[PDB]
Image: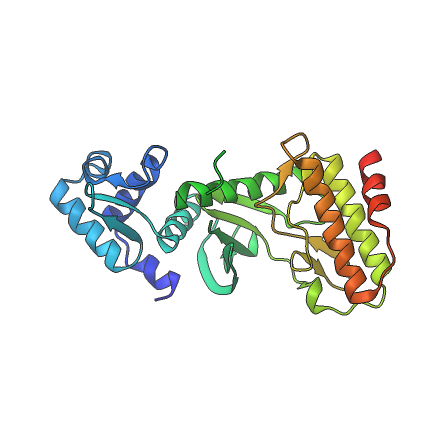
Length: 269
């Protein structure tokens, strides 16, 4: 079922049940039916019936091992976040999937206010909570993007739930483009890294999959793992972005940039 058709299957009572789960995620993975019912102002047996149907539509996951509780699936959280974007007037219609990997599904959409853009639905102490973590990923990307506006990143329009609404950049990932001036493209990427750093942001996963290129220039995308300068490990995270991108150029193009100097140059600004 496409996300547009799924959206059409939702009534007001369906959205009120989802609003109740969403607002109780801060203290439950699986929100108890009794609290879904009381928050939504929908009687228990009817709330139950709604949740069963949402489960059949793969919007929520219901469990009953310890108690009757519910949470969002990735599909459901995304659909709910889209609803929030639609009710806030930021999005008018969701369109076709643009692509999907391990971390997000990105869809085309149209907004009367922002034009033809994209909505990115995010997935995913003690090294060893789907919704809370996805929503944190989305908000992190959003704040990073806001702090970087005016640099070579998408314009960012809104954040709700696990969804970030932003500019469509018409440019391919670096890994699919043979460039003929690799030394200059590498230098432009490292300059933009230095510009991020002066804004207090480290990207956190810079690679050939999140640098976009066209004859016009480069852009950098995908900030859910970004950190603020001063946060634990930020310097090593920065060094890793520099190292990884330079390594990419060395292997693909035999560019001869020295990693320690490049890092040292950025950090001394």
